[PDB]
Structure formats: C-alpha cells, structure tokens
Image 1 (spheres, helix red, strand yellow):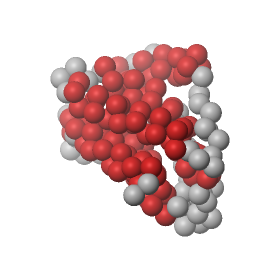
Image 2 (tube, one colour):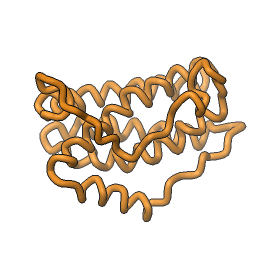
Image 3 (cartoon, rainbow, N blue to C red):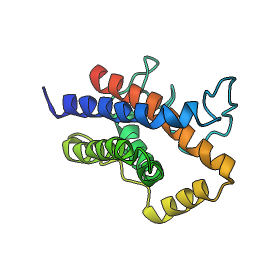
Image 4 (cartoon, rainbow, N blue to C red):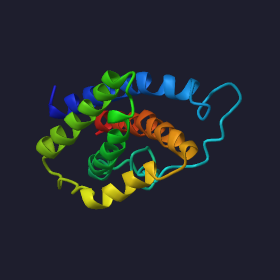
Length: 166
C-alpha cells in the first residue's frame, strides 16, 4: 500500500458522498432524471478529461492523467463550494464529499513525487466562475449542481482507474 493507493481509496469516498448529493438533487431536481429525461445539455464550464488527456487505453499516460486530476480537483473544489453550503438539509453529506475532495488535493501535492504540483486556478478568477454559476436564473442554477455531480461521478471514476493502472 502506498500514498497512491490511499489517493484512490479516498476518491471512492468522494463518490459515496455524491450519491447522497445527487440522489435528492436528481430525482426531485426536475433536471436530472425526474421521470421523463431532463435535457441536461447546459454543460457547465468544468471539463477536463478525454482520450487526448491520456486517462484511457488510447495512449494511457501516467503523469499527464494524474496531473489533470490535481488541477481538475482544484476547479472541482470551487464547484464543491457550490455544494458546500447549498445543501442546507443534507449539509452534512455535502461536507462529506468536499472534505474528502480536499484530502486528495493535499494528499497529491504532497505525495506528487515526480510530478509538478499541477499549479491551481487562481481564486480571483474562480470567484467569477462561482459568481457565474450563481448569476444564472433559478433554472440554470439547479442545473449547475446537477452537472457538477455528473463530473464527480464519471471524472473521479476515471481518476481511480488511472491511479490503479499507473
């Protein structure tokens, strides 16, 4: 078992939270899977994973994929701020997914041997992105929380298979 093995075991907890953070805000969200479809074609602005990154069999890299995970978790952190207080009923569950998602940001920058820290998105610019998720109508607002849990589910998933394939 190495610090990397703990990095994966920690992301698995991140998704366990998203379950309690995407079950209520998906069925009773009329914008995820109410009972018809819920065209979620908004696509927030937090993309960062594909076949070019190297997080899949096609050119499965190692330092390029894990890198996208460090900066991918920092941006994910501002979106966690979204679900860090928006959850007033299950606020505890929202803190269970954010606290862990932070445990990976520090556990990586520290155990990122043979890496680069992957820098991080300035908080001043991330202040405008967050002001933008909240500057959307009530409709686009409930959708922002949806797509966020959509990346955490998939995005984090590939992060685990990338740390195990490394």
